[PDB]
Amino acid sequence: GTEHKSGFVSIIGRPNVGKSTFVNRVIGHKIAIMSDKAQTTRNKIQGVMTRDDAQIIFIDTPGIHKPKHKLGDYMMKVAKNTLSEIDAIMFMVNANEEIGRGDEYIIEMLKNVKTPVFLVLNKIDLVHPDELMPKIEEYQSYMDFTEIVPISALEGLNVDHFIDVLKTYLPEGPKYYPDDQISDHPEQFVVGEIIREKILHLTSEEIPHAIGVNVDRMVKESEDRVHIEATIYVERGSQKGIVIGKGGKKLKEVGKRARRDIEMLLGSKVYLELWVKVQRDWRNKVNFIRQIGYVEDQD
Ligand SMILES: Nc1nc2c(ncn2[C@@H]2O[C@H](COP(=O)(O)OP(=O)(O)O)[C@@H](O)[C@H]2O)c(=O)[nH]1
Ligand SMILES: [Mg+2]
């Protein structure tokens, strides 16, 4: 059934295990704006895999392979949060090497994580087929995994099957990054769709319910802190009370919930400003926008 899936996955593992090889294989042609414009939030979008039936956004976690003295108290909190918000974890491991401390350090960080962890044995091309099941068993002694999938990221052996399996674990969801619009960085579409989801929870309906979200600005204030301006657009000012509510109470709750989901996923602390505006037809028209709503969220 023809029902579109989308989500956030993080590819974790020690250096030289194949993470960028995998990313660059599956994502296809690299998005141009991602190397013009730097991303304001912390947790870097690696790229966008779009098939007809699904879209996956690859997010960087912090270096959970690192020992605790190198990745501090704060960047652990960011890493554990990001791993919860994410839809799936790709734990990528070298088939051709013995288990080092870096993989034990990752296993420690995945202990009280409830997100699906996929064990991806990479570099199976450097190894006899009968070597895979013993190595799988080495890792299974440490923890349970959701699926175990041997690949070669370089050759492409078993990659498409891995993606088919990975897609089954995604929720139903929007195409975050579209084909029409090359101009803005995909982080803006991630924030835009998060805001929109919080609005559509309130609607919760099959009254025909048209609402839009624009993100007017995203600005890095610090390595932790980002300022988002966004305008929610509605038809009909009587949509106050779906969206603004009794003295702004409903718009605060949207602002609070969207701020949290942006902080947890993308790893930067936010100062969110939301506007709510009514848009009538604009083509050859004067005074088609009336504001009905403003909120401010932080700390
Ligand atoms: N033989 C083999 N080499 C691979 C495979 N995947 C990646 N490599 C190579 O192993 C290295 C891994 O580096 P990279 O992909 O940058 O991994 P990262 O540090 O995890 O991003 C590169 O020299 C890749 O060409 C694979 O499946 N088989
Ligand atoms: Mg590398």
Image: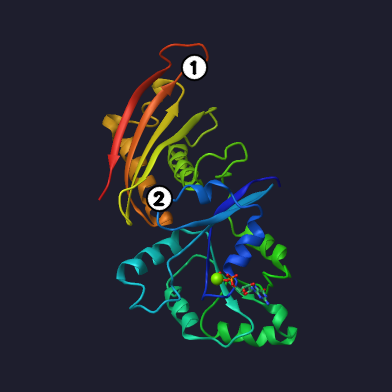
Q: Is residue 85 above or below residue 180?
A: below
Q: Is residue 274 left or right of residue 53?
A: left
Judge depth for marks 1 and 2 and give the one in front: 2
Count of number-bearing discs: 2
**Image point (52%, 51%), residue name:** 35
Circle 1 SS class: loop
Residue 83 seen by the camera: yes
Q: Position of residue 121 (x, y in %)?
A: 63, 76
Q: In the image, is residue 5 above or below residue 106?
A: above
Disc 1 to disc 2, C-alpha distance: 32 Å
Locate residue 94: give its quadrant. Answer: bottom right
Indicate left or right for 28 with 289 as reference: right
**Which label sits on residue 282?**
1
Q: Residue at x 48, y 46 (%)?
A: 190
Query: First in sequence: mark 1 or mark 2?
Result: 2
Q: Residues within 10 Å of mark 1 (few under 14, many from 20)?
A: few
Disc sitting over residue 40 in the figure: 2
Secondary structure of the residue carrying numbered label 2: loop
Whether label 1 touches label 2, CB < 8 Å: no
For the residue marked with disc 2, what is the amino acid? Thr
Picture layout, residue 43 above or below residue 5: below
Three-letter code, disc 1? Trp
